[PDB]
Image (spheres, rainbow, N blue to C red):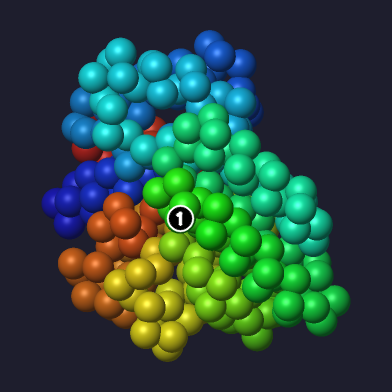
């Protein structure tokens, strides 16, 4: 009802990945097939840079060329070496990424260094925007933990030109929570960047009910029209099965 509407909405905002690994060509091909669901396409697939060329061919051949290819750089570590983060980002662009999700140097921020996060994000944004590629910034809210640090990483990422702020890599003990999702969307609101900055929930949401709860935070803060594919994603694998079950598939 409300849950079927929210489940279809969430499905169309998914950056689809698998739990175990989508980096053998056969697993990347299977992921591309999975993204083309009976009720619509996911917003994107999320894969490692080396998987992009075969993913692009697979998406074209199955007649879903508008499924975005998102990838990851500086990942999953969020090290504070800008030259490495930037080189990986330029490689991701060259492979053919539509979007790059770079990991913010969160341990550097936890050690009191705000500048390196600004400089790393800004360099990667400039490279991506020069190639018409969107930059998401993974702040790893589940490692920052402290509300003030989650706000500060979000603020720095936005000031440095992030097109999205993303909770998590998906590969640490704590990924998204409803609390970190709310804090990060509060920062988008408080900085006046709702037009230019999206929010991505990585992990946390496992069920159709969870997806409804996470979207309800966006609807509360920004109104129900805000959370389109340019402004909201679910970084998810197992969630898709739950959304399809809520919609009467499997």
Return the x and y of residue 82 as percentages of the image width and height: 75, 58
Q: Nearer the viewer, residue 120 or 14?
A: 120
Q: Does residue 7 show up?
A: no
Q: Quadrant of residue 216?
A: bottom left
| Point 54% across, 30% down: residue | 95
| Point 39% across, 53% down: residue | 233
Bin the neighbour count of mark 1 within 10 Å (Cα to Cα): few under 14, some 14-19, many 20 and up.
Answer: some
| Point 18% across, 67% down: residue | 225
For label 1, the residue is 129
| Point 73% across, 77% down: residue | 115
Q: Quadrant of residue 142?
A: bottom right
Horizontal relation, residue 13 to residue 185: left or right: left
The C terminus, quarter of image: top left
Q: Nearer the viewer, residue 128 or 202?
A: 128
Q: Is residue 82 above or below residue 23?
A: below
Q: Secondary structure at mark 1?
A: helix
Return the x and y of residue 121 as percentages of the image width and height: 62, 64
């Amino acid at each position: 009802t409300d849950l079927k509407a929210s489940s279809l909405r969430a499905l169309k905002l998914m950056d689809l990945s698998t739990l175990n690994g989508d980096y053998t060509d056969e697993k990347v091909i299977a992921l591309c097939h999975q993204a083309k669901t009976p009720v619509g396409n996911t917003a994107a697939i999320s894969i490692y840079p080396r998987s992009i060329p075969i993913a692009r061919k697979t998406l074209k051949e199955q007649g879903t060329p508008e499924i975005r290819i998102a990838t990851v750089t500086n990942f999953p570590h969020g090290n504070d070496d800008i030259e490495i983060a930037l080189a990986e980002t330029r490689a991701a662009i060259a492979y053919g990424a539509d979007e790059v999700d770079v990991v913010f140097p969160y341990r550097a921020l936890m050690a009191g260094n705000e500048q390196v996060g600004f400089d790393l994000v800004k360099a990667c944004k400039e490279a991506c925007a020069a190639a018409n590629v969107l930059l998401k910034v993974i702040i790893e809210s589940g490692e920052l933990k402290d509300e003030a640090l989650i706000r500060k990483a979000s603020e720095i990422s936005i000031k440095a030109g992030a097109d999205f702020i993303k909770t998590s890599t998906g590969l640490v003990a704590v990924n998204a929570t409803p609390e970190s999702a709310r804090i990060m969307m509060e920062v988008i609101r408080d900085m006046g960047v709702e037009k230019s900055v999206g929010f991505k929930v990585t992990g946390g949401a496992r069920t159709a009910e969870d997806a409804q709860k996470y979207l309800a935070i966006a609807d509360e803060l920004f109104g129900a029209d805000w959370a389109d594919a340019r402004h909201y994603r679910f970084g998810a694998s197992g969630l898709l099965a739950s959304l399809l079950k809520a919609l009467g598939h499997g």
